[PDB]
Image (cartoon, rainbow, N blue to C red; front, side):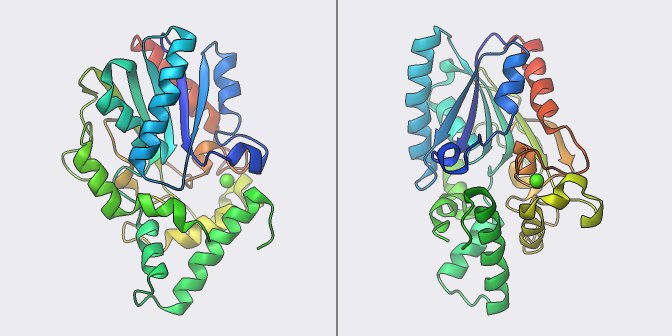
Length: 284
Ligand SMILES: [Ca+2]
């Protein structure tokens, strides 16, 4: 097991209550079976990255007091990695590692497009309908409601807002776009994972029964970056040392969603347990 406890981090504080199961579906369970100490920080989605960073620091302070651990190994997804980067930047002595999994480390082109849609910035009406319906299909599958207050979550994840975030917290960002950052910055280890939607939809296996997957493929087509997971471009995910980012998976497939339904019979959970063992091998 890892020297320092693992902290799974995501945005959407209410996910577990509203949906009825975890954001990192089946992943904390798997990690505990391999003897790791695991905790989950569910952060507020409808505010800034810096506010989520402060929220996570308070979580971490309370966790460290309760574990007598010196540091934490962050594994984050989407929003999570930015909040992890805030804590690591400001409180490096308490952070053993930041692992970014499909993190919005340089902004989301879909977030950019939603702002344009909300501001009515000359977005053709046929495009407006495909994006909102794709988002509604994704949210309905989780919440169970049959019906776009989601702008609240995407506001902080635009290319403009994340560029501003990166300006304050540049640690471990790649010098060249789509490249690799420094593995160790100020004592803290940084790693990234990623994915992008690949292949024709027919050969997706498990995802054929996941209504969110077709929705992610619609959103995929509106990116300027062709390699994207439906919400984030491949290059935008990069932070610190790359492990692997060519998985044929959409954004939520990489957190084993919906409820285990993923692409191409890939063992998503094994990505997390193998990385946990890798962290252990690095004396973390
Ligand atoms: Ca899926």
